[PDB]
Image (tube, rainbow, N blue to C red):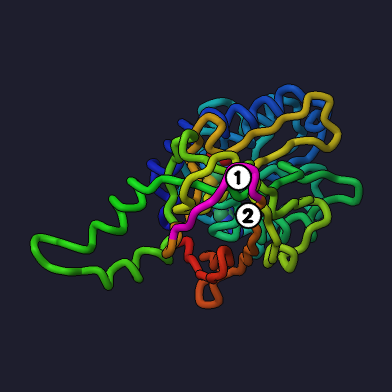
Amino acid sequence: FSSYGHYGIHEEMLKDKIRTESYRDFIYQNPHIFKDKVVLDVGCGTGILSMFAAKAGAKKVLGVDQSEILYQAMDIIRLNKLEDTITLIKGKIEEVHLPVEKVDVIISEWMGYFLLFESMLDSVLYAKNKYLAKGGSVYPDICTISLVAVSDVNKHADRIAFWDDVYGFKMSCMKKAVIPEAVVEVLDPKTLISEPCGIKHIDCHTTSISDLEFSSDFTLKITRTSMCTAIAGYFDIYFEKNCHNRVVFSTGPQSTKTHWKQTVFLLEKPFSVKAGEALKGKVTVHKNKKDPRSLTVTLTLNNSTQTYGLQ
Ligand SMILES: Nc1ncnc2c1ncn2[C@@H]1O[C@H](CSCC[C@H](N)C(=O)O)[C@@H](O)[C@H]1O
């Protein structure tokens, strides 16, 4: 997270209005969760979430960040005259000393592409287990991951078939290098050819890092006779617990784009499909053993298995 030291990443998250306004509406519409409480903001970045908490009436907010962005947060917090409520702490949540032993509320923007990329939920779960007061709460509290079948033969060809004739030379062996790299892009919802299928439900209050390594059967109900060229992944985020004004956002292709877009696993061998059909398959999501921040996602479908990496 040298990357998180740069303004660009933060600028992009703050320009993600669906994302930021969701956390804002949650905090502002449910002040009772925050009023007079002690709040921990895991990975506070510019301090945006910590300031939302302060405005909703938090007694004390600890903004923790490992990146150099923390120093901007310090200045930002002072600029807004919030330094008597929000403390900034520089370091990894799993190793910094905090000046308190328990907190009432943990808030965090931890989600990666396909929800789990970067493995920042591990860090939030660490904070939850070590610092959340008995009876306390962690937000967002519920998360889900869905898959949807895609048909886009022309896009498939632009990316894959590119390699067949490059300035007069065959480079078709490159296709074997292309297929395994999951693509992060916004999908044209016109190209969706199934109903979605949930593949994971996460309760952030009771889940363990162990549960974030998972298999799931899935069935996609095809809505359009055509050819399946890819499977897409996405996630929904819920703010529910203790909320009278409950907040949800989706990062699916049917919803307003976010900076997470969608994660797309291209099929090595696309295959036909009929409206009404129940397309059956299996997905496995594991940390990349060499780099636990990277994901490995294995799709079995139409009698073939393929492992994909998210960077
Ligand atoms: N284990 C960890 N300990 C402390 N900070 C972490 C961390 N893992 C990731 N981060 C920080 O978490 C931030 C996530 S980006 C979210 C930034 C801000 N809360 C916002 O909502 O806009 C990054 O700044 C990164 O440096």
Earlier-in-chain disc, 1 versus 2: 1
Q: Which quadrant would residue 210 be assigned to in this image?
A: bottom right
Residue at (55%, 57%) from the top-left corner?
117
**Is residue 132 depicted above or below 304 in this figure?**
above
Q: Badge 2 is on which residue?
A: 279
Q: Is residue 190 above or below residue 309?
A: above
Residue 245: x and y in percent read 78, 24
Residue type marked 1: Ile
Q: Quadrant of residue 19?
A: top right
Residue 306 vertical position relative to residue 129 in the rendered view, above or below: below
Instruction: Assign a secondary structure to mark 1.
Output: loop
**Which residue ends up furthest to the right in the rendered image?**
135
Circle 1/circle 2 CB separation < 8 Å:
yes
Judged from the image, the secondary structure of the residue bearing numbered disc 2 is strand
Q: Is residue 199 covered in magenta?
A: no
Nearer to us in this view, 274 or 254:
274
Specify whether 261 is left or right of 276: left
